[PDB]
Length: 169
Image 1 (cartoon, helix red, strand yellow):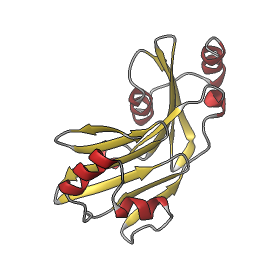
Image 2 (cartoon, rainbow, N blue to C red):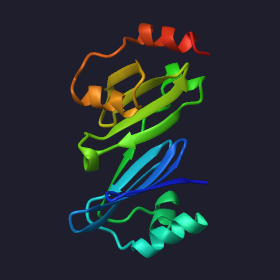
Image 3 (cartoon, rainbow, N blue to C red):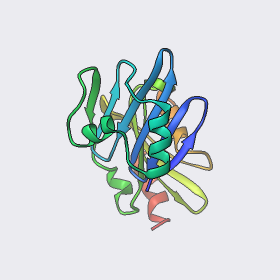
């Protein structure tokens, strides 16, 4: 079961560690898919109609393009990137995972996050340089960690974040 979020930007189908997003940008519809291990997105618009997106929403069957992607059959005009492992510091809390990419203004970023004690604990890493990391604890959304990363703002050290995680398990 995907949760579905529709907007003028497009459609977003989410699972705890998976996202299928269709963005009506520029010429037509571009797609982003990621699971726990792989990110892939189109460099050109794809042949997915709004009718197929309504059908995906109603029945829960992803379009054939996405099913091929989930089976490792990537289209020609697509970027495919391997993701890092689930953050070690968060691993024991069973975090969610989401990726944000150039379509919303980010260098490709993976974020692992949990809600704990009314706070968000998130670890964002640049997918292309996983050593660049923002560990974040705060009342905002998980995307805050990605924003701080983009803005090169200092974040929590490993020890500070691990204290927040331990005070949480």
